[PDB]
Length: 30
Length: 29
Length: 30
Image (tube, rainbow over all chains, first blue to last red):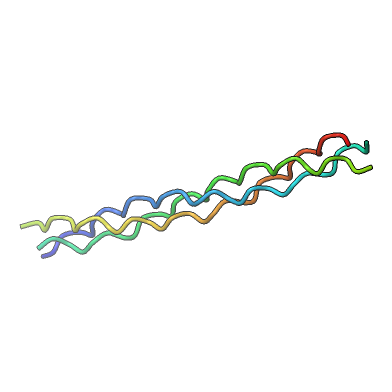
């Protein structure tokens, strides 16, 4: 009779980096 | 007679958060 | 005789993309 199921697959890879954040607030008035 | 293939692997981790944004605009007059 | 185990499963899917980064710092003085 055929044997047991094989091992689980390896984990997948880490996902891509997220998007760069938005610009900050305006600086102090000059 | 080997058995059937194993189950699919676990998902990978979510990617890192993006980098911080740039400085804001220069102060206006 | 005892059947050997099956082959490994397929690798997992990748993780999703990361979250957006934080806002930048305040701009420089005018």
